[PDB]
Image (cartoon, rainbow over all chains, first blue to last red; front, side, top):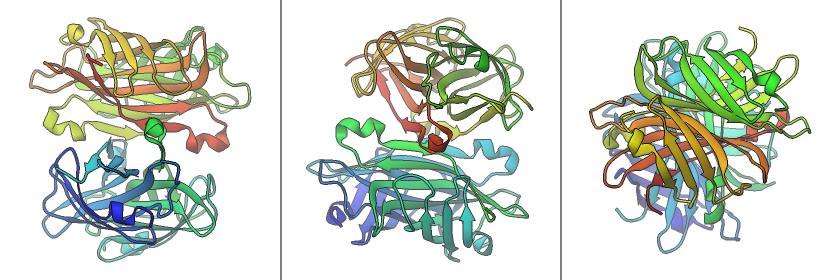
Length: 124
Length: 124
Length: 124
Length: 124
């Protein structure tokens, strides 16, 4: 992948969360997520995809991943998906928007989904 | 997984797209996505996660998945993440919201991300 | 406005909420909103804007409005904005997506905003 | 309103856009928006609402507003709604998420809505 080397490794967001990812040559993302906030402790499995052959015109690299908030410690009956782009260079960044859906009854489904934005850096 | 059997198989959304998924006992989602609309043709790899031990109180099952819109035919330099819940029973449904990010330059990044909502059924 | 007549009146969404709006020739939307769900009772003031000179090519009419969830009965310390399009004709519809932000502390601001989608019809 | 004085005035976002607002004692927001990016020039009318009696516990003040992107110069057949909270003090901020819907045909409605996030400050 063009940004395989650039994406693979440890990232930190503005909340102090830790995103540990391996980018496969084939577009795969695999790793672990540790949230600094919410109904979470320790690492959770993540999986996703990225564009392994991005535009060569200075565009970012599109990518996304999911965490289901179940591990050996806790179950928050919820999943977050991050959707965004990798921007390479001296201060490389992953700029995301995310959707967090909780399991709800049908009557409460209007209130099921939070939306926010996370920015990941290699330092922090 | 509680809904492993319920989730695994072929789903269709309101646009006529086809979502082919296997739910692993361990929370994994793997499969293929075929979009009826946009800069896409044929199937794309998807991966995600779901809550393999949901609440037993009538709540849905939280889940999410990603598609990077690169395959052997086309590259739309973009990724969609669906975040939502599986609702079991006679008319089982996956109710989602999604974020579609395109690779952009830094100057165009304000305009990088579409948001929408898809509902998947076993028929259609 | 092209859709001034079409927009003005009483709308109902999929939750059974009631949206009472007047469209001004100048792009103004004014009226009241009554939610069937959440920390709400009776009517709340709404204001917004719409495109009073839409495309004549079969496109919908872009529009949006806000409700702050404070009235003489209750204060949910929150605001919803609906963003979407009016689609005219036999089964006229307002198709929206919405953002509901609650006042939070800085530490809880990651969890401040819900996202969803409402479809309004003239019947229901 | 508790934050009437705090909200009223000129704000600037991270794109260099200018948001000129008056907060009414009654929860009204009125003013003008000038975008630094997109299919826009000069000022556009905005209207919205805010919580005129927020929590006294250090929570932000919920608020929202709409711009329809039609003025005497241009018509982008679109509307943006910002939903977020005012945070008072030395570096006062309005933290928002926004939905931008364009008028579309029914076949293109899946692609109608952008989502992003703007942070407004009194300086810039």
